[PDB]
Image 1 (spheres, one colour):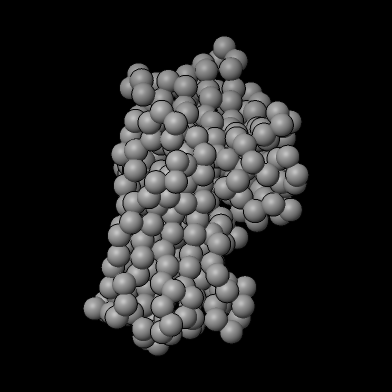
Image 2 (image 1 turned 90 degrees about the horizontal axis):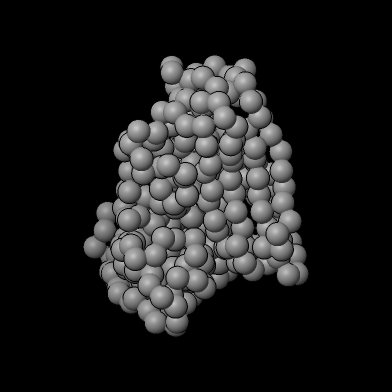
Length: 150
Length: 150
């Protein structure tokens, strides 16, 4: 059951206000207007949401996913895309996915980790993110939302 | 443009786990499963989301709204429903709406305030909420989501 949705405008996307690299497009999401972030091309791919641990209930396992689509112009995905959750104490969940195998123009959710908040970690920043910083061109990824479920 | 959605499971609802007063129902919201909170009847109506100011961008006016519906069994709305945003420094936006005038079985958004985060208020808890604590029975309110736009 989904507790929060965090749209890309709330994230920090490196080069996200440079129209050479990223565009933004308004779409309806249920009753709301959201803007999808549409990657044209970068070598430095980096998207990071930050939300406080106090936003969440303690002693409860949450899992987080990002909803994305590969465009008709998709290339450069044969590399590992890093998936990260960083907790208030600096500890991290870290995993990777290869998107090159995926079909375009279809929404799909990538799981980026699970966490539970106990003791010290029940307050302070939590980062949710994904990145690839290799010197190859990543093209044609549209980002819909971060979802946090429990 | 909507930056976050916060579903009721993330909120604190007084009597929200008592099945005499509230029920919960799973529904599809775009690609996600959410649970609407369905008020049967209470005298003490109180729903509060908490999210940190650091979740948001500074020097930017945000507005917040709650999406709700009145059921076929709706009564007790001829009173003022309090709408509140409490900022990290303890200051508040406070307003009120009378729902008795509203038609049931139709989703509608109630604006609960605007805020901007500058200086000290760019970190620390922000509460978003609504309440009525009068000794009359409030019946038949379903709650879909808190939305924060900018």
